[PDB]
Amino acid sequence: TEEEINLTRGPSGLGFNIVGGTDQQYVSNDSGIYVSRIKENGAAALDGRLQEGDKILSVNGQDLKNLLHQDAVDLFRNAGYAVSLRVQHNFDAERDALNIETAIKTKGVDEVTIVNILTNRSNEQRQDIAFAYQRRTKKELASALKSALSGHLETVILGLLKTPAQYDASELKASMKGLGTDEDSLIEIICSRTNQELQEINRVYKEMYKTDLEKDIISDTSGDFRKLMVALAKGRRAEDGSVIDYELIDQDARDLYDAGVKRKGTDVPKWISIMTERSVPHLQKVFDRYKSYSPYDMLESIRKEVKGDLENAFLNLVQCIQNKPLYFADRLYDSMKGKGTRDKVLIRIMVSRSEVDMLKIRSEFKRKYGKSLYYYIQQDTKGDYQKALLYLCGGDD
Ligand SMILES: [Ca+2]
Ligand SMILES: [Ca+2]
Ligand SMILES: [Ca+2]
Ligand SMILES: [Ca+2]
Ligand SMILES: [Ca+2]
């Protein structure tokens, strides 16, 4: 609510304290000026309209806009004795929840407004919106949208309503439930996640499904492929050390060579040890030093040495080590380049990465393919589903 308040200044000021400004912003999450306290017997106290927490929108009939804290203090002191204040009595989450509700309950469902809200809010902001929606309607927002939406738009929106660890845990469960294991989706998640992401995934997975992620992996996988996936999911890769171990970079490169191209067969345990335990910056230098010894680089060496799920997992792993944004750019390109769309891949990347490194993915994509990721999404998808993806993309080029 907005009310205009007229006060008369006395020798002790207008009678209230202010906080905020462009140089604060950590006290209010924006640049606005807010009333924090009302001094008793001051002008604002006897008037009774000004409240603690009000946002000062206007003073003497000028909209406060991008003011430093001292600039607002100078504005309140030079306003004269008769001052008019246009005030405003997460309120953002409460508003977004109400509009989503009216959108869901609009005849035919306002899918546009739902997308415009949820795809243009951060993940934490979406959690707040979910809290306010359930308090107001006594119904779960995802459940409501699951009935309201359909098709690929439902998949996107429902994915966005999960925390990052919940979404990754649910996609990992989906890739193993039943008899057919989706190795591509399992490999994509396990290979591309950081130690911090995986430690939280292992925690959330246990809470959601009452079973350790490692145990579901052991059930649905076998062979060296099982060993590589169990190793990566532990999320205890060496953290980036302060020193570059050149001796170890060269020896690791020699060990990868001797384990594969140089011999008949492959010492797969040796490959798993090096590529899961060493830090990522160390392994990037290892893969370059490997080119000094081998006529084929690490990816070509993998194609020549192993096959099937093991090959696919190693190829995805080396790409993520070498260049994670380029990895997702290529997977995005693969999901869209030919007939139809691999929507499950396209959606999972856009949901999971839009708030992590979507600018780097778009940069790599545009430089490699000459057209923006935006463009490719535009061509391959349609409708509010397309609009959702384009918002997660963030912009053209
Ligand atoms: Ca409609
Ligand atoms: Ca539905
Ligand atoms: Ca299965
Ligand atoms: Ca070999
Ligand atoms: Ca296509």
Image (tube, grey):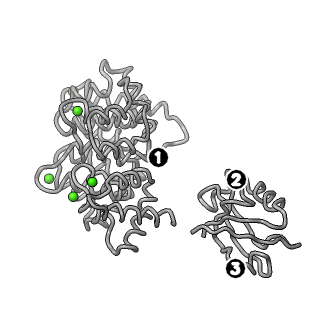
**In this rendering, position of residue 176 left or right of residue 325:** left
Q: Tag 1 or tag 3, which sits nearer the N-term?
A: 3
Kindly give the residue lying farthest to the top in the view shown. Answer: 295
Foreground label between 3 and 1:
3
Task: Find disc 1 in the rendering and name its residue.
Answer: 239
Circles 3 and 2, Cβ within 8 Å, touching? The answer is no
Q: Is residue 145 above or below residue 321?
A: below
Q: Tag 2 or tag 1, which sits nearer the N-term?
A: 2
Q: Position of residue 4 (x, y in %)?
A: 67, 67
Q: Position of residue 176 (x, y in %)?
A: 19, 53
Between the residue at mark 3 and the residue at mark 1, the CA separation in whole angstroms equals: 58 Å
- Image quadrant containing the N terminus: bottom right
331 or 215, which lies in front? Answer: 331
Circles 1 and 2, Cβ within 8 Å, touching? The answer is no
**In this rendering, position of residue 242 left or right of residue 173:** right
Task: Find disc 2 in the rendering and name its residue.
Answer: 23
Q: Position of residue 25 (x, y in %)?
A: 64, 56
Q: Quadrant of residue 28?
A: bottom right
Foreground label between 3 and 2:
3
Task: Find disc 3 in the rendering and name its residue.
Answer: 48
Q: Position of residue 385 (x, y in %)?
A: 29, 46
- Image quadrant containing the C terminus: top left
Q: Amino acid at mark 3?
A: Gly
Asked which secondary structure carries label 2, the reply is loop
Q: Amino acid at mark 2?
A: Asp
Between the residue at mark 1 and the residue at mark 2, the CA separation in whole angstroms equals: 35 Å
